[PDB]
Amino acid sequence: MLEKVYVALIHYPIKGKDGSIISTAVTNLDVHDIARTARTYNLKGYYIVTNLRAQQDMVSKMLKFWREGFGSRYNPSRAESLKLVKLKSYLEDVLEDIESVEGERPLIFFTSAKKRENDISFEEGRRIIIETEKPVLILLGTGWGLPDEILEISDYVLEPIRAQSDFNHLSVRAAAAIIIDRLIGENY
Amino acid sequence: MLEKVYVALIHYPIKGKDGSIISTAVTNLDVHDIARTARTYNLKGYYIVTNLRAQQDMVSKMLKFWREGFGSRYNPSRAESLKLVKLKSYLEDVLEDIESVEGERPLIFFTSAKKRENDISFEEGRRIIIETEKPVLILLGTGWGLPDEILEISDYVLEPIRAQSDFNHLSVRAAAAIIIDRLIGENY
Ligand SMILES: C[S@@+](CC[C@H](N)C(=O)[O-])C[C@H]1O[C@@H](n2cnc3c(N)ncnc32)[C@H](O)[C@@H]1O
Ligand SMILES: C[S@@+](CC[C@H](N)C(=O)[O-])C[C@H]1O[C@@H](n2cnc3c(N)ncnc32)[C@H](O)[C@@H]1O
Image (cartoon, rainbow over all chains, first blue to last red; front, side):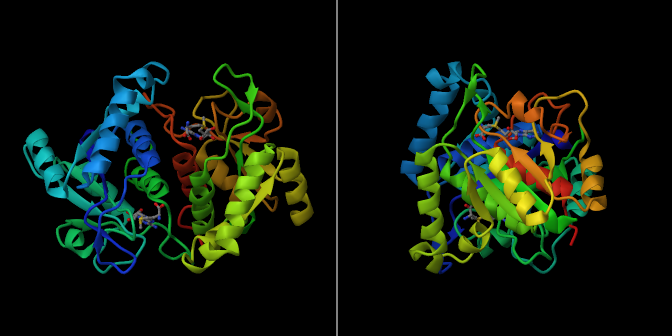
């Protein structure tokens, strides 16, 4: 059900340009942007996943500015949307947290512009979320996309958005928005 | 039809916090982000509308870096998506440009998180785009939203995304993504 859906923005492990594994910087706008989308569709949590202590520090400081500091008193909803945000160092820590919260490890939905074998449609994904009592975790990449090691542990790969177009390389913010709208939509 | 749809990001006239009319800075990521969304869904053009010469200069320089300069040789598709981008000083200049291109002034679709009287659903909007031979222009706001003077000249107001939610204050990048997916979707 729609009150048990999570999203995670992955910064490590991430594919580099030579796809080697890299660890990306967190772009500040990604935190605010995807938090607002998650909040709008009543998702349970938004995880920012990064093993870079400099990034963890920047995100933590930013979070308390907007959640506790001056920022929390001149927005309203920066802070409302940002309450959903949790920082974690690794995907495994995300999985462990959801298991603690939900009593159960989540179904993992891999996302990619690049067509994979054995994927599901968004209609098929919506059906799963409707019919399941399991928590669902939507994974979003940075850099040059989510790596094979994460693909290997994903339960489902959602088909690419606009797979038959001549161009479908969306930002992660635009992709997240569309993915969440297709899966949750105007259902309350 | 889907090969005659435009999007414009409005920075002036825009509602300020006291909603007074203000002129907003163009956030660089908005140019790249919404260009990719427009390109993915095969929209005809993406207008960046700003009457601030400092903003027009920053955007122009950025455009040629990615379209002509070094940027054009180490992406592929930054430059592909950015080809859709046109800078204009005023909404009127956008309308005038589309009239020159299409032989006809466009139908204007106003967008807002805030519920208005006399709006259309996305289903109703999709129908218009399917059945029309007129160009369509989707307007997106910055700051605290599109002002009444722009509302007054809009042919249609699309209903808010997630109007019945307790929170629907999306970023313009996330909103644009969802609006475009709802109107165009997986239609080729
Ligand atoms: C490759 S990353 C980096 C993209 C870009 N450089 C940016 O500024 O965000 C984009 C991420 O968004 C998601 N994404 C982008 N396009 C998508 C599509 N067409 N279908 C499904 N997911 C997509 C995937 O999760 C992907 O890992
Ligand atoms: C008010 S502006 C500024 C929002 C935010 N400060 C940002 O960083 O983008 C957001 C714009 O995105 C569009 N928008 C946002 N939420 C929307 C919604 N729920 N339904 C339709 N359009 C929306 C509107 O065009 C609006 O003018």
